[PDB]
Amino acid sequence: ADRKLWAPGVAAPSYLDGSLAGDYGWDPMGLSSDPKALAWYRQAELVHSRWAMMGVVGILGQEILNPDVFWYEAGLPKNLPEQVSGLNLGGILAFEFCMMHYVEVRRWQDYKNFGSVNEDPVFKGNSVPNEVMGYPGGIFDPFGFAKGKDIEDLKTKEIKNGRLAMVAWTGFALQAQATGKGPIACWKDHLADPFVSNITANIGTCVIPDSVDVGGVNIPLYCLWPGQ
Amino acid sequence: MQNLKIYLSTAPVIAFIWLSLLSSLIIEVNRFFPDPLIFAF
Amino acid sequence: RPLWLPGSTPPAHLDGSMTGDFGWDPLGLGANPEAMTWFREAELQNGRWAMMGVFGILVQELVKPDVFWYDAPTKIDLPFNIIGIVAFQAFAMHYVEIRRWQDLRKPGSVNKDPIFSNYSLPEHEPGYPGGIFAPFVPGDIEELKLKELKNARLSMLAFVGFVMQAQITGKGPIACWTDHLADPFGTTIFSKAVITLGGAVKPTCQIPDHVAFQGIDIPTPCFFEGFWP
Amino acid sequence: RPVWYPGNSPPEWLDGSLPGDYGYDPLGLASDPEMLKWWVQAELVHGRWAMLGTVGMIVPGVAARAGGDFPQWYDAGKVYIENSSIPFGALLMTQVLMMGWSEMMRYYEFVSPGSQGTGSFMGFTEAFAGTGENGYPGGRFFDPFGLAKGDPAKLQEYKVKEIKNGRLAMFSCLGYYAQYAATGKGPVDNWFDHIADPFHNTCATNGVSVPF
Ligand code: CLA
Ligand SMILES: CC(/C=C/C=C(C)/C=C/[C@@]12O[C@]1(C)C[C@@H](O)CC2(C)C)=C\C=C\C=C(C)\C=C\C=C(C)\C=C\[C@@]12O[C@]1(C)C[C@@H](O)CC2(C)C
Ligand SMILES: CC(/C=C/C=C(C)/C=C/[C@@]12O[C@]1(C)C[C@@H](O)CC2(C)C)=C\C=C\C=C(C)\C=C\C=C(C)\C=C\[C@@]12O[C@]1(C)C[C@@H](O)CC2(C)C
Ligand SMILES: CC(/C=C/C=C(C)/C=C/[C@@]12O[C@]1(C)C[C@@H](O)CC2(C)C)=C\C=C\C=C(C)\C=C\C=C(C)\C=C\[C@@]12O[C@]1(C)C[C@@H](O)CC2(C)C
Ligand SMILES: CC1=CCCC(C)(C)[C@H]1/C=C/C(C)=C/C=C/C(C)=C/C=C/C=C(C)/C=C/C=C(C)/C=C/C1=C(C)CCCC1(C)C
C-alpha cells in the first residue's frame, strides 16, 4: 500500500511497490528496472549506506577524541599514532588488500548465484542462515534480535539512517574540502556568526594542495569543483 | 553497388578512366625519363 | 563437487572426470578432446620437473652451501667441461624422451625393454608409467594421484616466485623467507613499488647483465623490467 | 539487435550473422553480396594488423619511461638502418618476397577454398586447408593451441571479441597517427602529458588541430 511517496502527487513506478525497505517510489531516472539491475543497485545502496554510517561516526569519533589532525587528511604517516608511524603504509595497504579482496569476492559470488555458498569453508560444518541477498547474520548478528520480533521495521530504520549518512558524510567531504575544517569545527564556526560563516563565503576556494606526497612525488589531489 | 558498377561499366566512363590511366602513365614516364627521341638508353 | 571458486558454475566440457578437475578454464582449452589429452601430459611434465626443481633450489641453499642460484661456479666445481655435459645431455634426454613421447601419441608400443624383455606393464595411463617406474606405491589409491597434482601445481606456481624474488630482491628463496618474518610490513613488493597517478617507483634489478663465464657474454637480462610495479 | 545510431533499422541487406554486425553500412558498400565476403576479410585482416600495430607502438613507448633506450614508433625506421648492418634494399625486397608469398597464398584460399592444403606444398595437408569461414584459417600452424576446435558456442563468442577489439585497435591506431602529426611525440608520452597537466595538454592546445 502507498506509504507516503516522495513528491505529493506522483505515480510509484510499476516495479516499485514498497516490498523493499525504504521505498518511497522515487526512481525518476528510471535507472532501476529489469530487477536484475535492482538487486545489484540495492546491494550498493546497502553497502554504501553502511560504510557511510560507519564513516560518519568514525569522523566524529576522530575529531572529538583527537582534537588535532584535520580529518580530510589523516592518511599520511604524520598524523598516525605512536605504535604505528613507521609501519610503511605500502606494507599497511598490503595487509588490507588480501583481507578485503577475500571478503568482497566472498560476497560478490554470493550475489551471482544465491544461497550458494553461505557456509564456512575450512571447518565447513556451519553456515549463516537464510536471507535475501545481503541480510546475513548467523554470525553477523550475534545478538539474535531482528529475527522473531519486527524485522523489516529495523530494516526500515537501517536505510533511513543509512541514506542520512551518505548525504551527511558527503557533507563532511565537501565541507572539510572548502573550509579546511573538521565537521564539528565548521559547525562551531557557523553557530558563532552564521551570516558570515555561511556557504556564501569560502566557495571558489578548494584550499587543497596538489602534491601531498609521501615516499616520492605522489598522490595528486583533484578536489571536486575547480575552486581555486 | 550492383547498379553503381553497371554504370561505371558504361562506354564513356571507361573511356575517361582508362585514358586517364594511360595519360597519367605516359605523363609520368616523361617525368623520370625525360626527352626520349630515340631508343638509345 | 569442490571447485576452484566455491560458488562457480564449472564450464560445460569439464565435469568431474580428469584427476583433480576443479573447473578452471577461463579460456576453455579443454573442450578439444585431442588437444586436452596433450595438455594433460604437459601439466604432469611441467609439474614433475618443477617439483624436483623447486626442491632442488631449497636444498641447494639451506642445508647446502649458500650461493643463490645463478651459479655456474660450484663446489662440485665443473668436473667435466660444460660442452662435455651438454653433449651428453642432448643424446641422453633425446632417447629418454622421444621414447616416452611416442607412448603418448601411439600408446603401448614402447613398453618393451629395448635390449631384452622384462617389458613394463599393460598400457595403463599414458602419463603414469607403472611397473618399474612406480614400485613402492606409498599410498594405495588414486587419492594419491590427485595428491600429486595439487603438490606440483603449487610448485610450478611456487617456482615463478624464485625467479622474480631473485630478480629484484637478489636473494635466494629461503633468504627472503627469513627476511620477511623480520619486520614483515616491509619487503612486500607492495610497499616496495607504487605507480599511482603521478609518482612511479620501481625497485631496480639487483642482478646485473653480462655475467662473465669462461670469457663468454651471457647477456642474461632481467625479465621485462619496464613493466615491473 | 543493438544497432548503431539507435532508432533506425539496419540496412535491409545485412541483418545477417556476421561477428560484430551492428548494421553500419551508411554508404552501402556491402550491397554486392559477392563483395561483402571480400570486405569481411578486409576488415578481419586490418583488425589483426591493427592489434599487432598498437602493441608494437605502445610497448617500445612504455619501455622508454624506465629508460632502456628504444625509439618511438615514428623514427624507429631510421634508428634501425642508422645502425644498419644490412642494406635497406635487401630488407624491403625480402619483405616483398616472403610477405608476398603469404598474401598471394592467403588469396587463393579465399578465391577457391578447396585448394591450399589439398597437398603438394611440402605436404602440410589440413594445416592450410582452412576451416571454411572467410578470415579464419584455423589449423595446426595458425592455431597452435587447438582453440576454435572445441565448443563452438565459445568460439562464436571469440569471433565477436576479435572484431570488437580490432575495430578499437584500428580507431586507436588512427589516433597514434593523427596525434603524432600534431604534438610530435610518442603515444605514451601523450598518455602521460594529459595525465599530468590535463588542462593545458588537451587537444585544443596542440596548436595544429585548432588553427587560428
Ligand atoms: C547556478 C549557476 C552558477 C554558475 C554556473 C556559477 C559559476 C561560477 N561561480 Mg557561482 N554562485 C552561484 C551560481 C552559479 N555560479 C550562486 C547561486 C551563488 C550563491 C551566491 C554563487 C556564489 C559564488 C561565489 C561566492 C563564487 C562563485 C564562483 C564561481 C565561478 C567558479 C569557477 C571556478 O572555480 O573556476 C576556476 C577558476 C577561476 C574562477 C579563475 C578566474 C579568474 C581569472 C579571470 C582567470 C585566471 C585564473 C586561473 C585560470 C585559475 C587557476 C589559477 C588560480 C590559482 C587563480 C564560476 C564561474 C567563484 C568565483 O568567482 O570563481 C572562483 C566565487 O568566488 N560563485
Ligand atoms: C551521497 C551518496 C549517493 C547519493 C546518490 C544519490 C542521491 C542517487 C540518487 C539516484 O539514484 C537514485 C536514488 C534514484 C534515481 O532514479 C535518481 C538518482 C538521482 C540517480 C553516496 C555516498 C556514500 C558515501 C560513503 C559510502 C562514504 C563512506 C566513507 C567512509 C567509509 C569513510 C572512511 C574514512 O572516514 C573514516 C572512516 C576515517 C577517516 O580518517 C579516513 C576515511 C577512510 C576517509
Ligand atoms: C607456473 C607455471 C604455469 C602456470 C600456469 C597457469 C596458472 C595456467 C592457467 C591456465 O592454463 C589454465 C590452467 C587454464 C586456462 O583456461 C587458463 C590458463 C591461464 C591458460 C609453470 C611453471 C613451470 C616451471 C617449470 C616447468 C620449471 C622447470 C625447471 C626447473 C624447476 C629447473 C630448475 C633448475 O635449473 C635451475 C633453474 C637452476 C639449478 O641450479 C637448479 C634447478 C632448480 C633444479
Ligand atoms: C591496419 C592499421 C594499422 C597497422 C599498424 C601497423 C602495421 C604498425 C606499424 C608500425 O609498427 C611499424 C610497422 C613500425 C613501427 O616502428 C611504427 C609503425 C608504423 C606504427 C590501421 C588501420 C586503420 C583503419 C582505420 C582507422 C579505418 C577506419 C575506417 C572507418 C571508420 C570506415 C568506416 C566506413 O567503412 C565503413 C565502416 C562503412 C561505410 O559504409 C562507411 C565508412 C565510413 C566508409
Ligand atoms: C571521497 C573523495 C572526495 C575527494 C577526493 C576523491 C574525489 C578522490 C574521493 C576520495 C576517495 C579515496 C578514499 C581515495 C584514496 C586515496 C589514497 C591516499 C589511497 C592510498 C594512497 C597511498 C598508498 C596506498 C601508499 C603510499 C606509500 C608509498 C607509495 C610508498 C611508501 C614508501 C616510501 C616513501 C618509499 C620506499 C619505501 C615505501 C614503503 C614504498
Image: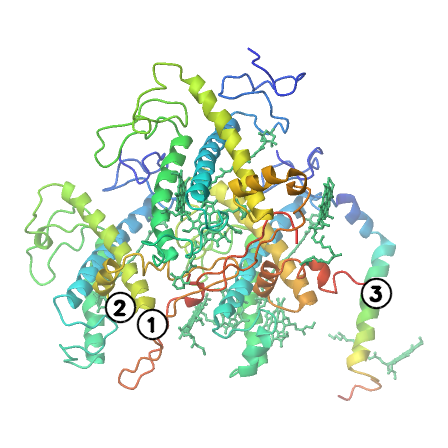
Query: From what the image shows, is residue A11 above or below residue C30?
Result: above
- For the residue carrying disc 2, how many other residues have a C-alpha within 10 Å: few (<14), some (14-19), or many (20+)? many
**In front of the other: label 3 or label 1?**
1
Circle 3 is placed at which residue position?
B20
Q: Which residue is mark 2?
A: C171
Chain that bears disc 2? C
Amino acid under disc 2: Lys
Q: How many marks?
A: 3
Mark number displayed over residue C206: 1
How far separated are the C-alphas under marks 3 and 1?
Answer: 67 Å
Confirm or deny contact between disc 3 and disc 2 (CB under 8 A). no
Left or right for D31, reference A79? right
User: In the displayed structure, does residue C146 sit left or right of residue D52?
Assistant: left
Q: CA distance from mark 2 to mark 1?
A: 9 Å
Q: Is residue A154 depicted above or below B14 in this figure? A: above
Q: Secondary structure at mark 3?
A: helix
Q: Residue furthest bottom?
A: B40
Q: From the viewer's perspective, is A175 left or right of C228?
A: right
Residue type pointed to by label 3: Ser
